[PDB]
Amino acid sequence: PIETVPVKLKPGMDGPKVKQWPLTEEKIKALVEICTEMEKEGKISKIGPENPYNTPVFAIKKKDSTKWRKLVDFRELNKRTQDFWEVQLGIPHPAGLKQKKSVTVLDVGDAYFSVPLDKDFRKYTAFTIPSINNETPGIRYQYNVLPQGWKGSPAIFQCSMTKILEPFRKQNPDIVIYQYMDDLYVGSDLEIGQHRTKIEELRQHLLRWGFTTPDKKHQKEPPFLWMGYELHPDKWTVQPTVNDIQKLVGKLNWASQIYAGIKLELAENREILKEPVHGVYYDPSKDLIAEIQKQGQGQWTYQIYQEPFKNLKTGKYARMKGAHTNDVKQLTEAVQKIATESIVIWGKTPKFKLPIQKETWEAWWTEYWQATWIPEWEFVNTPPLVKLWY
Amino acid sequence: IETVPVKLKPGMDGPKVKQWPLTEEKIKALVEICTEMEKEGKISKIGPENPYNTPVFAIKKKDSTKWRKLVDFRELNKRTQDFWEVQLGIPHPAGLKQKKSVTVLDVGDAYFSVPLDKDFRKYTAFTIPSINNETPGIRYQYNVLPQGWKGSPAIFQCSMTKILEPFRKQNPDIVIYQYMDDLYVGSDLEIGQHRTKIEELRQHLLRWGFTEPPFLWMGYELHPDKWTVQGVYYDPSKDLIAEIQKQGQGQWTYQIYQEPFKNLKTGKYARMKGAHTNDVKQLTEAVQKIATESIVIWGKTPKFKLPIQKETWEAWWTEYWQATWIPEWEFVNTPP
Ligand SMILES: N#CCCc1ccc2c(S(=O)(=O)n3nc(Nc4ccc(C#N)c(Cl)c4)nc3N)cccc2c1
């Protein structure tokens, strides 16, 4: 139903005619049954001898299942297809951005097989399954939909997803939609009934565009535990020799986000882990406030919050390994780093509450040789002085 | 009309550059501009089959009701064809420096009128990002001659000369120079006469264009003779460099030269407005002034050496930029 995306191969390159070798009889019968079912569903098509291209195929026994899955080695074709649009995107911030009252999840497992493929590129997906004992030529097929394991299937699927869901987001700017693994997560601030009607409308929309989402309600629990972050409608939490030190350092770094106080330091780590914590979500109407604490020895701890006692985020900044580094220089690097992180995560740089005297920064600028970015800030009386001396 | 064939430098692929994150209001303004452009048919969406990327961001000119979109075609300009020595266009007049008055004008809409070659439109794709990495950005490509690309003036040369003949024939001393969108009108007369002639040329252009933008009519004045006079020679082949340094109490000192220890030009700048408290604002204004001065004096915008941290400059240079183009800059982290 959706329009196909034209795609070609790298110039000066030809289709895969790689030789294949015979397989087992039960495996070939399973492959025949799977191919017949796909032909019934339209995901596959028959091609005559005019197409000389051939690609390997093999069956893998599913874990604790009678049926075997078909897998086609696309390693040779992955170097034939043109380059696709790859995006170097970092993992989204731990849900710090915005809040939705109610959340539902849906399944899009079959959607990977509902996207039509380009007509010019179909004949390159040719694979053969030889008959038993090869007394007669085997059966040759090519895909009419996106094939699994192909290089360009994820990018095409993502673009199709975005183009399908653009109008729905246009009509309802309040409702947020994300796609994690095979689960489409929808979040809304509206009431239960309105959210239900909107979800049914979205399901009918996706059916109209051909993508399949089951009627049966998904069994996923409210704690989604996505990317090591326990996610709840109101709050969020972090996950509860030569190689042993790196593992411990990594496990200590992740726990420093919402379990504030992470710095014989094993005892303090165990003590702070015993205290449950939580983090509220960002609110757009209220402005952001970031507070700084000088822990010492080149370490700073920053807390981002809207209102006091409700932290949006917590983090730690450490000085760069050099011969000498001034205290105010570390402070400025920390504040600009927090500003950049807030720009990425929320979009608006926050105002700061720093334990520094106003004239100190003015003297610093009069003395500094580079150019630094300084936002408006309000001094707060805190025991750390960080006067910078002289 | 029939389109003009353009190509690339052989052995060179298209540009792919990462897009830096932007704030909320900048993204809203960019979305509005791009929606208007797509309604006008000068911008079209693309799928994932195009692996070429180019940054885009919004600036704000003085007295702007809406931001202005700006694209960083530096990678393409480096990687596009040698289309400007065989089709060089017009050599820069040597009269720009001696006159007392020169006024800048914007002619971007005339560029937007004429269409581009089809088999090149893939290389001018840009991407508007999203906040919190929530969704992939929105991708676009140009259907007409783009702004900030040096191929547009080279292609438009003929139409530009066709409409510039009467004014130049009126009096040979008043000269016109083109550089990207910028159109410099140079005269050595009184301010009133210069302004009247500038307005005459403005509605001359408006009368030629069948399709009165407030941004188009806005321009600023520059006085080359006000500068110090005190280079011995200049080599067009070599690329020149301009170094910026910070002097106390919001002062800045810039040196333009092709070879070290031989200053082609030296200058100082300062403005004690009170909104100067941002160092990046003062640096951006200084760098724009230096680049405009070099463009009046010489053909091309120079290379720049910025005394600033990489990430701070990268994050806080966009909002204070006001020019129509982007120079090439390099960061220095060693004190003098
Ligand atoms: N698995 C899994 C998780 C699914 C998910 C959802 C959204 C994401 C967004 S997001 O843009 O759609 N988004 N998120 C929130 N916060 C929020 C509030 C309440 C609940 C509940 N219950 C939830 Cl799951 C999220 N606010 C906005 N705007 C962005 C990035 C990454 C995401 C991953």
Image (cartoon, coloured by chain):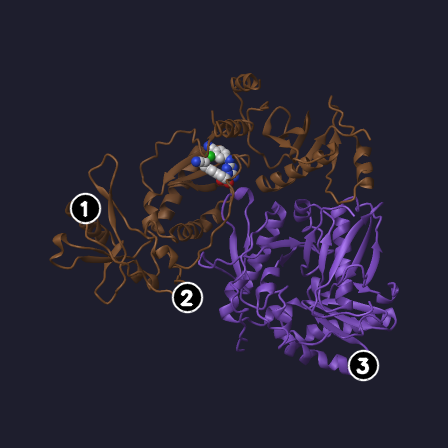
Chain colours: A brown, B purple
Residue furthest bottom in the image: B169
Residue B4 location (% of width, % of height): 55, 76
Residue A336 in which image quadrant? top right
Residue in the foreground of this view, choosing between A216 and A366: A366
Disc 2 from disc 3: Cα separation: 55 Å
Chain of the residue where label 3 is placed in the rendered structure: B
Residue A338 bears which disc, if any?
none
Residue B76 location (% of width, % of height): 58, 63
**Disc number lying in front (1 or 3):** 1
The kind of residue tagged 1 is: Lys
Which residue shows up at 78% across the image and 28% down it? A387
Disc 3 beta carbon < 8 A from ligand 1?
no
Residue in the foreground of this view, choosing between B336 and B162: B336
**Labels 1 and 3 positioned on one and the same chain:** no
What residue is disc 1 on?
A27
Q: Earlier in the sequence, mark 2 or mark 1?
A: 2
What residue is disc 3 on?
B171
Residue B104 location (% of width, % of height): 75, 66
Q: Secondary structure at mark 1?
A: helix
Q: Are marks 2 and 3 in contact (CB under 8 Å)?
A: no
The answer to whether residue A150 of the structure is visible from this angle is yes
Q: Secondary structure at mark 3?
A: loop
Q: Quadrant of the C terminus of chain A?
A: top right
**Labels 2 and 3 positioned on one and the same chain:** no
The answer to whether residue B210 of the structure is visible from this angle is no
Q: Are marks 1 and 3 in contact (CB under 8 Å)?
A: no
Chain of the residue where label 1 is placed in the rendered structure: A
Q: Secondary structure at mark 2?
A: loop
What residue is disc 2 on?
A11
Residue A56 location (% of width, % of height): 26, 54
Residue in the foreground of this view, choosing between A202 and A183: A183
